[PDB]
Amino acid sequence: GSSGSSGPLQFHSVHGDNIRISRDGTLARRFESFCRAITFSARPVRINERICVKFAEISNNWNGGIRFGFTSNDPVTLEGTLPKYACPDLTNRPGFWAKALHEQYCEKDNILYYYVNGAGDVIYGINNEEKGVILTGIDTRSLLWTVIDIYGNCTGIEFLDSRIYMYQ
Image (tube, rainbow, N blue to C red; front, side):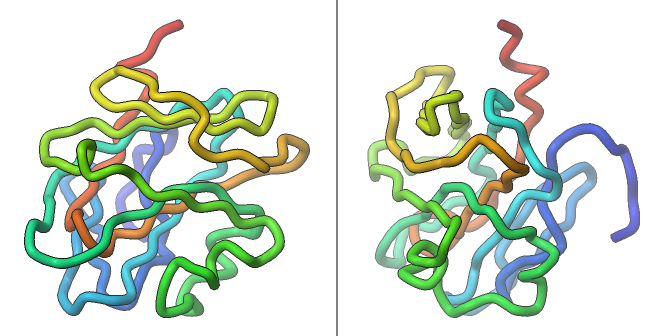
């Protein structure tokens, strides 16, 4: 709610119990606790639509890692109604995808970007360096939304505009 600047990609109202999403422009930071820390996309991104996320804050003490994927249902139908974790709950369900990232790419000041092709293949990359198809099974018929859980080696995350970086 509040603010504006329609166009760019930002965080959706729906967020974990202990998730404070608010910044001068757009950023998602944790409030407290450990569990309950799921987040979705503010607007429906397209297949080729590339997404970027700069790791603002990182946690180096807890155990586990983060998760990133796509979904079918709308993020508005999940607001104030999310599970305790991002899986198997947020995954086994019909039309839900999620994957984990390596520890080598779990640092601060790192730009985590990832997209999907017409072959339902999701490819990610760090520091403008793709890694390949990490997630699959993504449909390309109807709208789609992204998903990201911050619980482990990450605290704050700021979504960037791929339009500013990418060009091709």
